[PDB]
Image: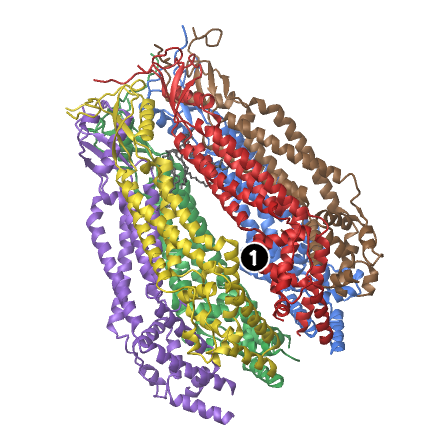
Chain colours: A purple, B green, C blue, D brown, E red, F yellow
Amino acid sequence: AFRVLKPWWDVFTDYLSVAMLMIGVFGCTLQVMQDKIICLPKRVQTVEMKGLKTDLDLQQYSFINQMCYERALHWYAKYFPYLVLIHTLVFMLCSNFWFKFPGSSSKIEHFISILGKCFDSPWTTRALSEVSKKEGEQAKALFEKVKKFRLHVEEGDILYAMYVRQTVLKVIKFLIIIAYNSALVSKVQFTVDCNVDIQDMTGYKNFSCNHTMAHLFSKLSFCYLCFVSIYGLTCLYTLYWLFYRSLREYSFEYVRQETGIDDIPDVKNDFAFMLHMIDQYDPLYSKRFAVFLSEVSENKLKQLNLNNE
Amino acid sequence: PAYRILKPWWDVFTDYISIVMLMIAVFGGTLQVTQDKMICLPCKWVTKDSCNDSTGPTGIKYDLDRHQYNYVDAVCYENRLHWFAKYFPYLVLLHTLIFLACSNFWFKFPRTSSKLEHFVSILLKCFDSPWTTRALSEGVLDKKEGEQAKALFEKVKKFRTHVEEGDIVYRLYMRQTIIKVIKFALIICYTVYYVHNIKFDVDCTVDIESLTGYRTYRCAHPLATLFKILASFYISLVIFYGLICMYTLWWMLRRSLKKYSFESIREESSYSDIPDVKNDFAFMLHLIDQYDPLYSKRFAVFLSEVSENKLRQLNLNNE
Amino acid sequence: PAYRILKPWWDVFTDYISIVMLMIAVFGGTLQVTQDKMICLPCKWVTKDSCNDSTGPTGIKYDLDRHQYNYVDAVCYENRLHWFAKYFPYLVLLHTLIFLACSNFWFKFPRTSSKLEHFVSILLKCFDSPWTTRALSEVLDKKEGEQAKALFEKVKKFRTHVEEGDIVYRLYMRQTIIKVIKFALIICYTVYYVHNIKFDVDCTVDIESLTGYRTYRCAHPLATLFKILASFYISLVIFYGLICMYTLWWMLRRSLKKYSFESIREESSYSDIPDVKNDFAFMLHLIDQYDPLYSKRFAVFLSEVSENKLRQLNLNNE
Amino acid sequence: PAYRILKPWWDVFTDYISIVMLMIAVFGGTLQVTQDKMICLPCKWVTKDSCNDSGPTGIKYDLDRHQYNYVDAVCYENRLHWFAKYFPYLVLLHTLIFLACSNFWFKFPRTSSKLEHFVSILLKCFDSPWTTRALSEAKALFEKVKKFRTHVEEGDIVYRLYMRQTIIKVIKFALIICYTVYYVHNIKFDVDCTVDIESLTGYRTYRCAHPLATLFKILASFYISLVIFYGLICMYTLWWMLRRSLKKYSFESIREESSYSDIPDVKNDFAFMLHLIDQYDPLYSKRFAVFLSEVSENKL
Amino acid sequence: PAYRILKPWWDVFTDYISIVMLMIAVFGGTLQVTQDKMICLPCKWVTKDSCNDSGPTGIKYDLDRHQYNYVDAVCYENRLHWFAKYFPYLVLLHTLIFLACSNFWFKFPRTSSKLEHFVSILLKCFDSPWTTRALSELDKKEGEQAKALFEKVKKFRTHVEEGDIVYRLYMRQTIIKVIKFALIICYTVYYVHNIKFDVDCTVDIESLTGYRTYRCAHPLATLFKILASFYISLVIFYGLICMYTLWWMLRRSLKKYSFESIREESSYSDIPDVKNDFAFMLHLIDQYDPLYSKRFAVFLSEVSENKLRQLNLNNE
Amino acid sequence: PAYRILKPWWDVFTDYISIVMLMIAVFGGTLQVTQDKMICLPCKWVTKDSCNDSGPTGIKYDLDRHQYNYVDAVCYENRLHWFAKYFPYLVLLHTLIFLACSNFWFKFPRTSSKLEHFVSILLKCFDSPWTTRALSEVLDKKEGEQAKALFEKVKKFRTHVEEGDIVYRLYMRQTIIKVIKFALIICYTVYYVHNIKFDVDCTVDIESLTGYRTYRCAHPLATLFKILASFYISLVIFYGLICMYTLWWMLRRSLKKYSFESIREESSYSDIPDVKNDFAFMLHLIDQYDPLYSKRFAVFLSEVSENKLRQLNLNN
Ligand SMILES: CCCCCCCC/C=C/CCCCCCCC(=O)OC[C@H](COP(=O)(O)OCCN)OC(=O)CCCCCCC/C=C/CCCCCCCC
Ligand SMILES: CCCCCCCC/C=C\CCCCCCCC(=O)OC[C@H](COP(=O)(O)OCCN)OC(=O)CCCCCCC/C=C/CCCCCCCC
Ligand SMILES: CCCCCCCC/C=C\CCCCCCCC(=O)OC[C@H](COP(=O)(O)OCCN)OC(=O)CCCCCCC/C=C/CCCCCCCC
């Protein structure tokens, strides 16, 4: 189960990435339009006014339009949606980066399988009733399974460090995106002074142009900037929650406070990290899984099984 | 999928209204990209920054190129067309996306989503269980069916202990309702205020005399009446959405959804031991009552210790 | 999926007519969005704001720019072309969406959707029950007898649940009434305004200060096409009217809230099948309209004589 | 669909002809919507409202672009033949009515219920293990078959609806061929329009070129060919429903081949759909014979 | 679907080739709809009803835009070759005929019924565990399904050997495909050179325009030549596949299948030498996978039925 | 579909890369079909077939709109490079050929049958209830019959597939073709990507129809068709690198010999032989995807597990 190991901030970032992809696709379809920039030459040769004849054909106007689109419009105003698509693709790929690793996937699947089968175990409810037959043998087998999990997962710390790496990658990518987008968002202007030297072709040298979708691209850039800022705030909170409490150390003393048996130990490394995942999801899962960690609880279960047999 | 039981008639109504509103947003958006322009004609005689408006008739010669006309159209469309006429479909799309996010936030938020999927799964599988019909009819039972019945009883008990502790689902549904109704109020206020600025005839004065020769132009916005009727239809849809939202708020606040009394089911059957469920469990059971009281009636038989006593006795007989 | 049993011939016909109307609605909407325009040429000689209509021939020099022509087209399309000719496909789309909403509010409203799903499940379970064959014959396995008894109890519980109140019948009656009155209004205003879709329009918008001419003659190229999309649409509505009217007659020629099993209780030996009423009666009448065999083999689960026969048969097998 | 066997070769062949007719109708419809127009040019010189044609230099007409568009629209509306303008819509309507005639035998709830009952019992007999034992030499299934026979021999509504559908599908073919053949010569590339817009344009008569006429020609010819095929198929269908009586089916060959000779001669709607079964594959009918003979019921 | 088992490598190759030619037909038709115009400029100096072809300033033709459009339409209709105008429509029609000829095997009700029955019995023989158990050399449900399946196989074998309708239909389909391949290659190879970028039109519209001869450029002519070369290559590949299929049918009698190697490998050495249509569909099975015929052949020998009935007698 | 198991990480990576290349091919083709042209303006001053380039007012060329269109069409046909014109069609064809090379493994009927049968038995063994008990080391009649039939089918399928290697040979050929085509694509695209220029000097000699000899043209989509091409090249490089790694994965170890020493040593069933050829190849592919499938299947081929299964069946 890969949905359960995803906290609220991860789903929020996934939906923000989906919205950013939609913005990029809309910008690309905006760039599909043929009519992009409209240019007019400068210094052309009850008050009644008369029009200024520029003595230019339609083809000369089209040539001026394309020359000023290529050599006067800023590269950001032309290739913003493609950059948005690339950035949102990299953001989406790195969202499940700690999910797709082989060992990470194996330990996550083992944890969710063990936790789910513990959740439908009658003896968990039996031990909760004790705190506040055949199923005894199943509980003994599940205790050996929990010990196997402790030997199989706790020796490593790949998951927490790899999650920290993915979150740091998200934070730095948000920083770079915000930086260059704030630096280049002022380049998307309506009126552009185009100064291409096509005087030998059209007769004029200075042109004043307008980018027709400059306002729409500016609004799209500001919306993308707001989305990236929300993404960065979410990732900054993720970094704060990751680093303010040591996820290499899960204190089960909160279980010890209301539950009388004190034998359950303080798990370390990957076990503590994934238990913090499940605590962010639902703390009842951890408070129930706590009772399967003790050894004197196993001895009491063995005593009950000996009485039954 | 299986969440339809948790969506009452108001939620379905807002779901379909949001779908139609998104269709409106898409239609207005594609028209705005495609055929949104302003055909601008200069005023030959001006008087104090305004058009003067002073043997066969002959056309007025403006001596303007086609591209000077396009430049004038783009400049006046950018500068003097009201922002509402330019950004109505995108504002509608943003509002509908936020409405859909508010209506589907509790389905995606893990803390409430876990409780919701647990409730839906165990309630549906209790509804199709055979021992529910066996108990409500008041023999021999199959081994597999007996194991399913005892497992379902234990799961219902553990879920009842798991859910009644807090009221996260009730609080989230409440907050979604107030957010939706205040956003409806804001949407209707600003849309009604700014809906009259979508005009066919727009007088622009953009100071491009150095490039064209004329200063004031009289532009025609072709998609102004179509955008006006689209905005009126959007306002009507938002009005319906908001009225449904205040009905949902009144339904939430009139009674106490955090307290369920099973007096209807418990008096009807012989089981007088069914407890008065409270908190979040009571809230989603009230939602199911808004869908169908039969689901709650068939689920209440799993909350009584008399029923589990009879099940245990029959299972001991079978074993 | 399994709702096809609850759709009689009139419902299927109205669904197909609504689909065709939606097709012509999106067709006209595409035309109106993409090539809807108005070619307006000024009348050089005029008399009291009216078109006077008065060596090889030479073209009339109007001395108008292309953009002046575009402005004249836009103004006389906005001001003088009738609103019906401009917004007919949108009206057709809105009416088709309203008709579809009225047709599917039966299945989308949760209070009646739950009852409809329960009735469909119970009816299909009784349809596939082997004991019904024996019930229509006049040995079963333990599983067959057990499931027959369980579905007998389920049928009894469902009859207690649904027969208490009529919400399905009331909603169906209201939907038919709303569809009939919508057809009446649609036919009235469409027939009244279909004569304004004309190819030739004389426009007089007073833009002499911007163009130089007062009155113009305009050709609306799509108008004739819209005409063959309008009258045709009217015919469809007429069908959608008459069929719906028949449905209304079917809801008024007899009380659908009283289903009589007289034919079955006379043909079959079981004479104890009660005269079911209310929503149960209404859905049984709908199923009778679909296929009488479903109701015929469902009627054996409403009689206690068949229950006693099943109990005795199960005891004989035991 | 569920009636994969009740449709013989003529039914499926006409269905595919209808599909190809529908796609060419849609192609012609988008053709007429998107770029269908006509380019109209006046005759400058005149001799009794004509043009005389008394290096080379182009002829000036003193017409604006909008005057040309007005002439195009007016001549397209007035002097282009209505067939050349509404051929794809006529084809689309004809194919929609053809598909409605084909699927009304499927959509009517009484006939749909009867067909689904026969299909369900036929398939459950086809997958039944006892028919193999009978052919080598289910009681509730036999009683169901007898009850279905008593239910379905009461009326022949399915055969009557099939007959009516065949008559509509052949007379519509006749009308389509007559009118399309008569009017296919009105799709000309070069037309003459005399629309009397001299007060707005200055010219009276114009020569117009219809760019999509020739395509609309050959497609129409193509359409005619397809219709002919349809009609020919329908023609033989009429023969198939007039040479033999489909309301009475004889099981003589199967009951002679099989050990049981007590299979009665089936009548009515049962006979008609068993004739359809024999047209598709005789195995289904041969197999359903042994689920009908009362001698095999006594053996069952 | 269920007919995937009956289609050998040539059939699936032709299907993918045909869908590719449909893709190029759709592309060509869309481009012929959208940008199949031509740009015609009048020849200023006419010499013997032709073009003399005899700082700089542009040539003034005194023609409106609408006269240019009229000249374009008239010369596109009259003096452009019919191949350059109807290449995508002809390609679509040919591909549709190829699809119809390839799928008429599955749509003719007699042959479709035979093929569906063959597929059903082969698949249920694949699902049968007793078929594997017998080849390896008793459950009640296994015995019932087994007895039903051998009786099914005997009934099918008696049914299908009556007529070789399916083999003759496949022969006719291959012959139609190869002759249509020959005709397509002949006329397309002849007429592909007529797609030219530069054409000269002489349409006699001097009464309306003032010029007699015009020089026209067809912008889509080179793209249409590329598409025609692609179509010719695809049809050449399809035709070579058809040659191999016809040679496969004519190499050995497909109406005569011997199980000699199969019954020599297995303990059962009395599997009969089937013939006609059953032999044909079994040859197609061998073309797809010899394992299907390998596991199906045990249902035809009398020794296998004798031991099946002996084991049923032991069970009963 | 069912063949998701047989696709390792390199295969799904190339699938996503091919999907992205098809996406950019569709985008480039849409741009090429819709708005690919060039704006050509005549050069008033000509010197040695080139432009001299020796308030302000415009230059009057005295050319109609249709003369401009004719000049644009002729200089797009004759002087713009073929790579700039046909880059979207080339990337579309290359992506189609790469997808065909990827899926010819799945579509070839012999290898399709082998892969489908392998995947079917592997999925029914992976979900077999007997595997959990065997790994944990009475039997239900239905479950025992299913286990016995599954064991016999695994044995006979191993004998059926061990005879020859056709799946490995096709995979080898597909990887070789995919790397050779990658090399050719990179070479020719890198060589011809420099011909996509925004400014093109055209000289087409239409002075008789236009009046000018040399024109200067702007190709509006050139720069875009530059960067997309670069992007395309980047994707191809990635594709090639992945293919190169796959080629190395074919050569560093013998893919036709599989040893169960990773399972037979750990498990008590040390009697597992070394499978060979195609069976070894698909088992190595499973190990590339997930070793759990091969580990759970490995108990169904050893004979000690067969002995213990027969003992459990006898105990019932
Ligand atoms: C906010 C999200 C919005 C999502 C946007 C989706 C993608 C948008 C990008 C579009 C991609 C390519 C389409 C561009 C076509 C532009 C052609 C263009 O502008 O040419 C100008 C010219 C101006 O048109 P007139 O004839 O004056 O029309 C005036 C109407 N009386 O237009 C043309 O020549 C043809 C226009 C092409 C239309 C293309 C779009 C049509 C969309 C179909 C609408 C579907 C209707 C649905 C049902 C309607 C209600 C029943
Ligand atoms: C592998 C090859 C596959 C080829 C498939 C191509 C599909 C399209 C084929 C049909 C072509 C139709 C031609 C339409 C031309 C109509 C007249 C014309 O020239 O239109 C120009 C007009 C100018 O824009 P206006 O809206 O007027 O701008 C100013 C007002 N805002 O519109 C256009 O730009 C083109 C008109 C529509 C053509 C394109 C239609 C399909 C476009 C698909 C968009 C692809 C976007 C992909 C999104 C993600 C990208 C990473
Ligand atoms: C019953 C059918 C219902 C569906 C109909 C839906 C209508 C189409 C929806 C898309 C709206 C876009 C249409 C825009 C039209 C106005 C734009 C305009 O001014 O175009 C000018 C210009 C007119 O001249 P040309 O075509 O160059 O003439 C050359 C002479 N041979 O037209 C264009 O450029 C094309 C305009 C856009 C066309 C896009 C839609 C065409 C659809 C193609 C249908 C066939 C597709 C598959 C082909 C099958 C193989 C044969």
Asked if one can make out residue A61 in the rendered structure from this viewpoint, the answer is yes
Furthest residue toward right:
D262
- Label 1: element kind: loop
Can you give x and y, in whole percent of width and height, for residue A277 in the image?
34, 72
Using residue B229 as the reference point, say whether residue C185 is left or right of it: right
To which chain does the residue with label 1 belong?
A: E
Residue at image mark 1: E289
Using residue C130 as the reference point, say whether residue B124 is left or right of it: left
Using residue D80 as the reference point, say whether residue A157 is left or right of it: left
Judge by depth and name the residue closer to the eye, D17 or B164.
D17
Picture quadrant of residue D159? top right
Does residue A26 sit above or below F258 in this rendering?
Answer: above
Asked if one can make out residue B240 in the rendered structure from this viewpoint, the answer is no
Does residue E81 sit above or below E1 in this rendering?
Answer: above
Furthest residue toward bottom:
A307
Query: Residue at point 67% right, 34% down?
Result: D231
Picture quadrant of residue D87? top right
Judge by depth and name the residue closer to the eye, F130 or E280.
E280
Query: Residue at point 32% right, 84% down?
Result: A265
- Quadrant containing the C terminus of chain F in the rendered view: bottom right
Q: Quadrant of ligand 1?
A: top left
Does residue D287 sit above or below B221 in this rendering?
Answer: below
Can you give x and y, in whole percent of width and height, for residue C156 in the image?
67, 69
Can you give x and y, in whole percent of width and height, for residue B233 in the image?
43, 45
Judge by depth and name the residue closer to the eye, C196 or D278.
D278
